[PDB]
Amino acid sequence: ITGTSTVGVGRGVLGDQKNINTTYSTYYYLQDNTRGNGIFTYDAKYRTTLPGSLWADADNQFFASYDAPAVDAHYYAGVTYDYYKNVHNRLSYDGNNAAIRSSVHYSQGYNNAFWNGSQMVYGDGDGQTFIPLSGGIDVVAHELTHAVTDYTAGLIYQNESGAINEAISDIFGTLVEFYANKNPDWEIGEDVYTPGISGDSLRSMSDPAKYGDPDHYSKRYTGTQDNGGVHINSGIINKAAYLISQGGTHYGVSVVGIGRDKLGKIFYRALTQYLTPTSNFSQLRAAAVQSATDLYGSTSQEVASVKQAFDAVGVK
Ligand SMILES: CC(C)C[C@H](NP(=O)(O)CNC(=O)OCc1ccccc1)C(=O)NC[C@@H](C)C(C)(C)C
Ligand SMILES: [Ca+2]
Ligand SMILES: [Ca+2]
Ligand SMILES: [Ca+2]
Ligand SMILES: [Ca+2]
Ligand SMILES: [Zn+2]
């Protein structure tokens, strides 16, 4: 909408106060004009028709319980935009400052979040498996990264390419969480998963097997559920990425860590210059090796560590 840029204040899902960029024209809208061609957050009003209505508020204060998922979807989309722009010189998900749209309060009791081809969508959870999913910065960044993938490599959402697609979203979700630097970890979704259970998470990148996901290619899922295991087999790639960054010895194979920033550079280059819609795990290894070679040189520690990490997870 046309209006003047304003700064509201509110509380997110976890109870934390934050400032949010809004737009004033009669109402204060969740429309952040400070980033690209805008970040826009919508109310789906417990229904499934999208996007719903652009979030309108009378007083620019967002402290109601109903407001909290909107505050966080809006704010964490901004953090994710900043990560891609400042770290990778990428302007929004399409590279040309496309408007970023999110809807919250999608459906009833909805234990998921997704990119629908055009926008991000967040359930409120049922209060048992999830609380409102936009409360997780890694979750928000995971969703926006699906849009990045779709505009770049275009990894088909099934089987190995789909597990790579998933892992890319978990990797960059985690790197955005570290960028913001509030309680960062290598776990996925811990801030919004299972409010009655402390210390767990939806997935672990450091130890995928803690939640039953494979940490070696020989343990990959080969059935048809979950689009051929896209949220399961992602563990193999998540573990490789974790090892590249942090190092470790896994199934007897030692990996020298090179840190998160270099992990992000390698995987961003692989995603945007080498992967294709049909890339499989072996082709991801080759893309990561080539990316590290481009950035650091063929004789570099970074190339050697990429090879060690894929060896450790059984991907040749
Ligand atoms: C980061 C996480 C909190 C949320 C993330 N959402 P996502 O990976 O983004 C789900 N996405 C999804 O299933 O997309 C299918 C689709 C939708 C629309 C158009 C085309 C395809 C995700 O991992 N969901 C699976 C969990 C909830 C399980 C338990 C596997 C059902
Ligand atoms: Ca208000
Ligand atoms: Ca965390
Ligand atoms: Ca996390
Ligand atoms: Ca929990
Ligand atoms: Zn996903």
Image (tube, rainbow, N blue to C red):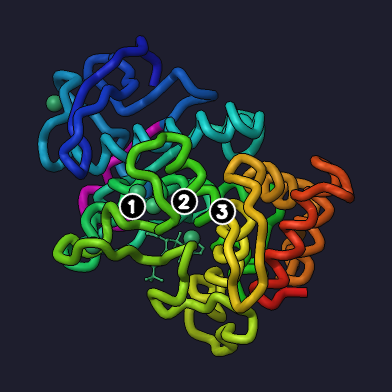
Q: Which residue does the numbered mark 2 point to in the structure image?
A: 143
Query: Which residues fall within the magenta stretch?
Result: 40-48
SS of the residue under disc 3: helix
What x and y, as percent, mark residue 192?
Answer: 26, 55
Q: Is mark 2 within 8 Å of ligand 1?
A: yes
Which amino acid, by three-letter code, is at mark 1? Tyr
The answer to whether the residues at label 1 and label 3 have Cβ atoms under 8 Å apart is no
Among the two numbered marks 1 and 3 on one chain, the one whose residue lies closer to the N terminus: 1
Q: Is residue 44 magenta?
A: yes
Which mark, residue 246? 3
What x and y, as percent, mark residue 212?
Answer: 42, 80
Quadrant of res 25:
top left
Q: Which residue does the numbered mark 1 point to in the structure image?
A: 122
- In the displayed orientation, state which residue is furthest to the left: 64
- In the displayed orientation, state which residue is furthest to the top: 4
* Left or right: where 226 falls relative to 150: left
What x and y, as percent, mark residue 230?
Answer: 54, 72
Q: Nearer the viewer, mark 2 or mark 1?
A: 2
The answer to whether the residues at label 2 and label 1 have Cβ atoms under 8 Å apart is yes
Among the two numbered marks 2 and 1 on one chain, the one whose residue lies closer to the N terminus: 1
Which amino acid, by three-letter code, is at mark 3? Gln
Would residue 129 be visible to someone looking at this image? yes
SS of the residue under disc 2: helix
SS of the residue under disc 1: strand
Q: Name above or below for residue 128 compared with residue 91.
A: below
Which mark, residue 210? none
* Left or right: where 304 falls relative to 108: right
Q: Residue at x 23, y 67 (%)?
A: 129
Q: Is residue 118 magenta?
A: no
